[PDB]
Image 1 (cartoon, protein in one colour):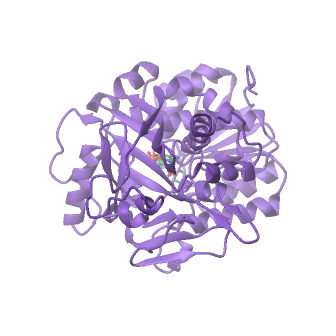
Image 2 (tube, rainbow, N blue to C red):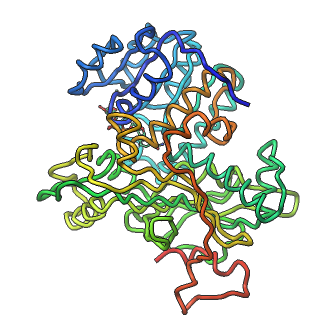
Image 3 (tube, rainbow, N blue to C red):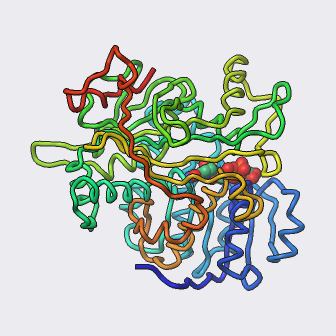
Length: 470
Ligand SMILES: NC(=O)c1ccc[n+]([C@@H]2O[C@H](COP(=O)([O-])OP(=O)(O)OC[C@H]3O[C@@H](n4cnc5c(N)ncnc54)[C@H](O)[C@@H]3O)[C@@H](O)[C@H]2O)c1
């Protein structure tokens, strides 16, 4: 059930005008006439293309930094009914803006629950209160307090965001193939009942970035297909993962949250040091980094089934195989005591020679072993679909556009996550920007090629976390 056309708002406000924000303006141009809209962008960093932006939409740019002092003064004159606040910044508290948008009655959209300046790596803050799990529980507590009201969709980019919709569709594919049941769940509980009935035990966000760089890294240069400092920051945080009801042995140097709706583990080691085996359509078995991610918790909680005596819950976490440049950069990064790099470079469309960003979810434990579903977007395809976009950026920008259109057509939903949306509508908005949406089955498991652990008669034994992590 989808709206043929969604009317534009009266005003848009971009808190932060970085890569993703710029990668998103072209996509937004096709949908809505940016000249009939008053569009603000608040960023302390003036971009080079700010002139072309002003000579196409009349972009009212504000060179300022949003902090606890001046945020309630730069925005209040700008926020109101009919305004959409799109937060694509760093160091700005999403939760702080949510409450502010509720007062002004404005719609809110972001791709990450960011705290204020320095909320991730703050030694003065206790560790267990610096995890994505804790950031999410703050959002959920604010969701309960505010309750019904103007919509605010958080953490809806590519991942977290689209991948949540991929999980739902993957479950329906498995349901049609294994169970012959074409019945769509109607609520969270029914989604969890389906995951349990199929026997889903492990879900990976298995991403493989095969994009090749035009030129080679210069000395001391950290290169990546998206934000370098955003990648280093996520790589530095402790690895987190949803812990499933099938697991037995616990990871080493690990702690756990159990006061919520499901077990959530955070390992006291950087995600860039925790390597896990996974599977992607690029070349099958792959090695990724167990990077902490929002969807690792939201997906697991979404498919958690708690009854009087039993509990069902899959293991869910990110498995990221980044570009060849980032891997080599991470290597040198460790060699320099993880100090901030001398030089940085986010690869642009002109810098990428070939390759694709395989972004999808890998569901495991069911009758057919492994099933991968997601977006396979090549760089060449992205260049023909929009400007200022790589394969990595376009998948995110598409996620932003999807959430943008949902909050306009559903502006009275309060605070919501990707799981609260209608995945069918969410993907139909932007399916054309995701290149190839395919589902691939595979008889793979982390023990198939390791004689020391291979088993074909113990059902869930091959799906234990000990078999995935190195
Ligand atoms: N869900 C996803 O798939 C996904 C993918 C990538 C990024 N993101 C998120 O989107 C957000 C933006 O990421 P990006 O890749 O474009 O990073 P970026 O660094 O290219 O852009 C972030 C921008 O925010 C600006 N900024 C920093 N402090 C600010 C302040 N106090 N006030 C206003 N602006 C400020 C910076 O100048 C920068 O231009 C991040 O929070 C990131 O976590 C989500």
